[PDB]
Amino acid sequence: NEVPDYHEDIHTYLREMEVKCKPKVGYMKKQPDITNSMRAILVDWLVEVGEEYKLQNETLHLAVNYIDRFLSSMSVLRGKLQLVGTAAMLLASKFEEIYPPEVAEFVYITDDTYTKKQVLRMEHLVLKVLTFDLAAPTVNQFLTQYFLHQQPANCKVESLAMFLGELSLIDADPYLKYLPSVIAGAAFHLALYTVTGQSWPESLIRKTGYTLESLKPCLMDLHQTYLKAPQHAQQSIREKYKNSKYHGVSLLNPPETLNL
Amino acid sequence: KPSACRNLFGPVDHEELTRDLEKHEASQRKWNFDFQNHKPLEGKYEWQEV
Amino acid sequence: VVYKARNKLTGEVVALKKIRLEGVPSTAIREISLLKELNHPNIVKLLDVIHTENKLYLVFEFLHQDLKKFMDASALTGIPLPLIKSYLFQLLQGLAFCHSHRVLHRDLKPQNLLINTEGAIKLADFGLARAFGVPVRTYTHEVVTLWYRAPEILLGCKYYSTAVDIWSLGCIFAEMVTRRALFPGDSEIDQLFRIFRTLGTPDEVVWPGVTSMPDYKPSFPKWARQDFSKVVPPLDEDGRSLLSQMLHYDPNKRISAKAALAHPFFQDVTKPVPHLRL
């Protein structure tokens, strides 16, 4: 599944695009009704939806990107927030999935809050606001590249890194401050360190230009998120990563301290 | 029935919601073409059909 | 395509495509979102997108016709080698750009390659394209128009990537030289057997892992590999070398588009106009 001839070109390109596809950090302050707490409720629900329809993790990450960019431009009352999230998941599914769920399934999974026509109209509106720019880089896209630098491959490290990257989607404060490549870096180091005691490899310094020093602010945040995860109001990601499919990594004990 | 099947923030006014969405010329000026109607317009683009 | 138009002030010509509106088709979602990121002289340019309540309009740069029609028009006349060489060189540039921007085209065939009177050729029709990841995940199976479909797809590989487009381009290269499809199969198994009869039935030596592929069968007849001088007789030594590298069985050994740009076959490449009036 490797594409050795284009790996570097693609990484460089994703590094260009993640700056262009970044949502506005302070957008929630400009929303009259919705809040970070409501956004967290929404994203946690999308995790469940992804589990119910067996969607890719990439699809979830894309949907969250679309939502944050949409809300960066458009004011939305709380009663319509789930409609935005539903259309984003529909769009991300069409883009990313081999078998996207039908619109009727998305309507159903909102417990029939909206109609089919409303979901389709919202899809239209999201596309207009995003100007059809859907091919966004995600934390997931960076993580899978970073995983190739494992010495050697460790599936527990990969699962834990994915878990930590997903946790970042829930909390706009602080994670909107960081680029996906940076969150991916922090997640990979934290997962690697938790499971093996090893650190961010020199080969990734060469590839990304990031060091433990540059990753530190994000790492400090992500370590706190990890430590407090069992107490978080939103638990769908923890439940998801208890699965043996993900080697039950959400059950691992985070290290009390890092060694930076 | 599945746990994922849930309403997050209450019932909505469908008439009002449909109204707000139904709401949503600059391109017509750029291309001198009427897209809603599928009709060419006189302009600097000469719309020969197929 | 239902409308075209020349601009008076510039002389530039555009084409108007329409899509009637499960909401917006996933093929349209991908085509538009990917084309917006693919600005290259050898990729058809998407100029604008216009959404209406039940219709989606795409404005493209206009190109005169496609390579299939051109080859059919030249069915009894040789396409001059300099033009074949120029077209292949340009197609490799367009494809390398796609791959470097994490896009697989997945439907390279002469009907999807557009040409103009100036000697340009451009990749078109990205409706079947997809943005890939590194490393790749399993994607949609049985992709690519049958005659141009790579053996890893035919054998049901869990993973495929950029090599599938290079395979198609190798088939198109051969087809330009003869104006006849290289592997004109009537079904998936017939397609596979036409490839085997030409390139030999692959074994573990030629393609490690091949006998473990989901749709490999030990009952496959075992055909010998024939010389490329017999596969495409008019092609010279450099041309045969390049073609053989684009049609390597093992996707990991198959030449990349950007590596192919430096092949000796292109040492004397130019940009001639077409030999027939468009």
Image (cartoon, coloured by chain):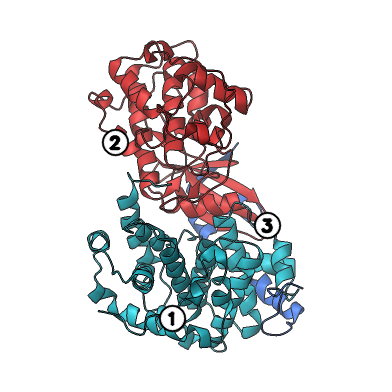
Chain colours: A cyan, B blue, C red
- On screen, residue A64 above or below A150: below
Q: Residue A39: x and y, percent?
A: 55, 81
Task: Tell me the amino acid under the disc marked 1.
Answer: Tyr
Q: Residue at x 68, y 73 (%)?
A: B4
Marks 3 and 2, Cα distance to the nearest angstrom?
Answer: 44 Å
Name the residue beneath numbered marker 2: C259
In the rendered image, residue B20, in percent from the top left (x then y), is placed at 67, 76
Q: Chain of mark 1?
A: A
Check the residue under mark 2 and report the chain it is in.
C
Is residue C273 visible in the rendered structure shown here? no
Q: According to the image, label 3 marks what residue?
A: C54
Identify the amino acid type marked 2.
Answer: Ala
Nearer the observer, A78 or C222: C222
Both marks 2 and 1 on one chain: no
Residue at image point 48% right, 10% down? C76
Gap between marks 3 and 1 measured at Cα: 46 Å
Which amino acid, by three-letter code, is at mark 3? Asn
